[PDB]
Image 1 (tube, helix red, strand yellow):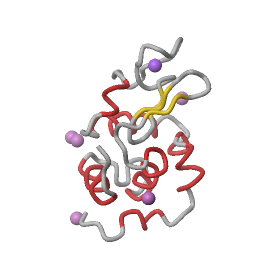
Image 2 (cartoon, helix red, strand yellow):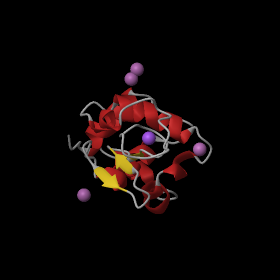
Image 3 (cartoon, rainbow, N blue to C red):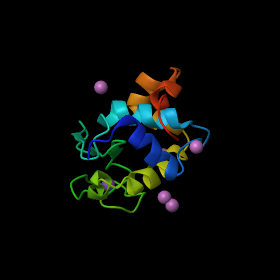
Image 4 (cartoon, rainbow, N blue to C red):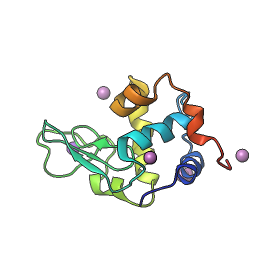
Length: 129
Ligand code: NA
Ligand SMILES: [Rh+]
Ligand SMILES: [Rh+]
Ligand SMILES: [Rh+]
Ligand SMILES: [Rh+]
Ligand SMILES: [Rh+]
């Protein structure tokens, strides 16, 4: 599924991401925009052979099992395929673990390079929340 901006903000809010570990909803929407262009089905292979999955580009080295990332972990205890669902529940639950891990939202390279320090409130402007 390719979400609209305000449609994703509403789903993220419902699933408890607004202010999760102090990160406003606009941070999460901005991250999803630059990681996946709001596409749940997005996949991107990494130089290390790991793959990033879903609306928040969650990596198979640490977070999910895809059966093709040797000596990786599955710290979210999910098949990476669960992260490509139209239902964002599994991505949001795994993203909560990731952002609690010590480097916060810097775990998302698109968030650090394109969202961090910017007017991220703009990403929820005009949305009924
Ligand atoms: Na893995
Ligand atoms: Rh939920
Ligand atoms: Rh819930
Ligand atoms: Rh766009
Ligand atoms: Rh870690
Ligand atoms: Rh509201």
